Image: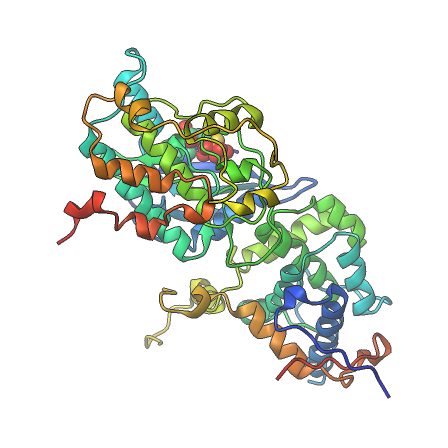
Length: 284
Length: 213
Ligand SMILES: Nc1ncnc2c1ncn2[C@@H]1O[C@H](COP(=O)(O)OP(=O)(O)OP(O)(O)=S)[C@H](O)[C@H]1O
């Protein structure tokens, strides 16, 4: 899939032209079918809009609302030369607010993103954040047999999912939000794993190992390790704080813990997340 | 005298074989009635294939391990195409070609496990390119509105290209299961309809499917 920048002729409004050629042993890319398909279902302000599709000969082009850069690009700009650096906390609460808002929407329509990360979070010059690339997403409203898929990075992958789980729900996306957050605060990846083995370790390093009493179902996990070097949870404050120049208040922490549980069922929901005291000021 | 299996309220906990029968039955029933009553579509074959509808379905079902939901969806895709593609009409001259396409598209657009068109084409009995365009066509006539959700057909209807008229014509919140009640709706429907051994494909499976009251 190759994309280009373009702009309406009738309207001056600019757009993004992702190009997916047609005719092949697989004909129309399932990814395209899945993307185009779900996008018509996701009309929300924090979810890149799919303007239209342009079929033609052996070339299909999806016309997305052109967004400037992304959470990833955005931060590098800030401190690409000054090594890792988090963002102003007011700004961390704002972007996190938009991400849960758009995601909250997805989950209500029974759709999981499945691949949330800094770069999959487009931003426009107006500072608006929107969820992107729904190529690996899926409508869980349709009870088919689930199967995780290959991603280029595992820095945002949930532990249980990495442990072979194929029965996860919306919970998978919440974990990513937890990671995304921590990264926005500290400026760098909270679990820079380099493979499923490495990642799990790093996650367990700070979260401790799974607690078969607070998370009994983990034994059902196909890649579970009955006899692994148990570890206690390291405490979050002393892991982040030292790399952030603002007192990580209480709420932020509690919230951060609610998104970063190991036991899926214990992970907060996007709905619940949006109603956590940490966002009180956005109400009333 | 004929057997009398009792099906589960959940089509997932139901025999993939039993579905294909219930679906196939319904399928030749619509073919009977639709013919009981011109311009060709990509789904038209030059003459009725010799292989029965059912014998064609299991094969596609077995050698491509099509999932349950994908089976139902295929059927539902009939009411979707018949509604948004006037020329398309389910009759014993379009069924197969439709079924191939329908089935291979429900799988790719809705499932985690899915094959390549060439695989599908091989099992289906056609040239890959034949299946490519056959899939591209259906996708255009529906505007990639393949997710079986309550208001899908309508939205699809609307989203169609509309003829300007002199006089003007004419959210899933709170909606049960967030609007994913189509596939069940149909499941229940087929058992109520062609549930008994009284359709036409009697020849296939001699069974009486009773769905719990
Ligand atoms: N709306 C957009 N605005 C600006 N640039 C875009 C937009 N969409 C795509 N791009 C560009 O295209 C690039 C990568 O192609 P992708 O859109 O991300 O396709 P994808 O492979 O389905 O998703 P991935 O896993 O993120 S590469 C970068 O995201 C951008 O440089």
